[PDB]
Amino acid sequence: ATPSMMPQWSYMHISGQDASEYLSPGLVQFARATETYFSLNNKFRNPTVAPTHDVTTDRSQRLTLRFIPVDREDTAYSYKARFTLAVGDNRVLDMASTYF
Amino acid sequence: DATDPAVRAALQSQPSGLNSTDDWRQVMDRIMSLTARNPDAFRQQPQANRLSAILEAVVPARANPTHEKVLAIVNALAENRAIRPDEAGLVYDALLQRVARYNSGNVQTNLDRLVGDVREAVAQRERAQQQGNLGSMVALNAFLSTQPANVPRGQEDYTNFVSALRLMVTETPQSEVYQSGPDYFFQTSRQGLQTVNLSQAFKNLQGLWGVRSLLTPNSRLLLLLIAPFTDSGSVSRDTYLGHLLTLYREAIGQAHVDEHTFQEITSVSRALGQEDTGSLEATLNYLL
Amino acid sequence: SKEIPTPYMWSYQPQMGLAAGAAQDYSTRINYMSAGPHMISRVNGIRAHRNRILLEQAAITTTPRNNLNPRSWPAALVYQESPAPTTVVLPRDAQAEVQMTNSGAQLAGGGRPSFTPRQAILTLQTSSSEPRSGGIGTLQFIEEFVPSVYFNPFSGPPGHYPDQFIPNFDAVKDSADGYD
């Protein structure tokens, strides 16, 4: 993402093209054919790159929240807990991540 | 006037009020009540304040200009960097001691000639700073004595390049040339980067003026700095140095409009609502 | 080293909001002491292609200024919050409730009253009284202070060097700071 860093990251294959793209087309065609008996796969670096934009914000936001019961109620055989599950502005909550 | 060594000496030695010696006319306008604003402000003073100003007016008190004449000289030596600001009290007592040992009618006249001489010398240095030419023209013309005036090929490109070389040091008062050992250099500003090596660049461009992967990056740094001072007709179109000087003028003009494009895109990416981390990286990868 | 130098990368100080001082990018260097001329020449063309990007990134993004790393950025050159004005819908009519209460009615709870059609709306300035100056934030430290590619380093007379690379140097003192 840094324009400064792209000449030496792409040269050392830290961020750039896969081995199906920066190698010559004769060597990719060779490595596909001879793969079952002479593999050239681990000889060439493939850069996996995480995206910087439109994934994760930089504002103040907690990962896990804590929710005090609004109205609890204790019976001799049961216990009740009523919560406010407030999902704030521009957030999503998968209810699999929720628990008591 | 804030950089005047005798105005600054009046703000450090002369009183901040209206005495009847330095300001005789301004206090006689107030004693005799012929002032425009508040004429009757002198009748409303006690006799200790009112009669002591009349006595200093009809027969005024003499004074020593010697501490004021020397302090105008010291505050000009401290301004033209001749002394340190820490030495401003050391050389003030050193000069007051000398004009006390050797005091005369000649010396007090000679201090009066020298406080008008240092008013000029402070202003002459501050004009020479904003012009910024005298230290550079004598050392760029000293460089061009070393370089030959007749290249074999492309003399038309060479004599307009070295004339545009005189145009950087003239039309930029901060830029300077000098020597450090064998070679000469060119800083584009005081205490700034982009220092080209003139003796290494002109031993690289020599042999490239008519050619029509081979340039040292300080020669290309020189061709970047000389680009806004070079016309399209100053060098050729097909010549490889002339082809780059047009290419570096387009690169400056594109970087001048990618600067204004950057200030537009990032302004409307904050209000529209984006990541402030990614608004500043996706813009540069769109502009670079 | 002089022709293709290593860029001075700036250290930020989040408290003062200024740059601490720039040291060279020693930690991103690439090791070609085991390479030959077929690959040393290819890496030196990447050291130089990076330095062309940083001069291009500084010509786009860095504010043109005389003193590199100034100590008090002006208010016109600092990114400042300019929000929309706050529109306040005032809840109650003040002089229409002092006439219901003086007449004997007890008001409790809470147009919004059934006894008043009047509705007051107040618009207030959200931004500060004075524009802020003195120190740039993190995002403006990113835009400015692009790493300085300093060609032919320290070739001048003393005093014409970048002393503002040094983290001890006061610009308005022209001296390096000490322990007291």
Image (cartoon, coloured by chain):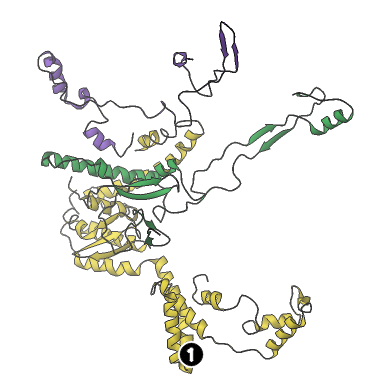
Q: Quadrant of residue B39?
A: bottom right
Is any part of residue B239 visible from this angle? no
Residue, far right: C103
Q: Position of residue B47 (x, y in %)?
A: 77, 83
Q: Secondary structure at mark 1?
A: helix
Residue A85 lies, with reference to residue C17, above or below; the image says above
Q: Residue at x 42, y 40 (%)?
A: B262
Residue A41 lies, with reference to residue B195, above or below; the image says above
Residue B63 lies, with reference to residue C148, above or below; the image says below
Residue, far bottom: B105
Q: Residue at x 10, y 17 (%)?
A: A38
Q: Residue at x 84, y 25 (%)?
A: C106
Residue bearing mark 1: B109
Q: Colour of chain A?
A: purple
| Towards the viewer: B248 or C63 | C63
Q: Quadrant of residue A1?
A: top left
Q: Horizontally, is B72 left or right of C167 in the view?
A: right
Q: Colour of chain C?
A: green
Is any part of residue B75 visible from this angle? yes
Q: Horizontally, is B259 left or right of B227 in the view?
A: right
| Towards the viewer: A83 or B33 | A83
Q: Position of residue B286 (x, y in %)?
A: 37, 34
Q: Position of residue C102 (x, y in %)?
A: 88, 31
Q: Horizontally, is C42 left or right of B115 in the view?
A: left
Judging from the image, what is the letter of the chain drawn in yellow? B
- What amino acid is labelled 1 in the image? Thr
Residue, far top: A77
Q: Horizontally, is B87 left or right of C48 in the view?
A: right
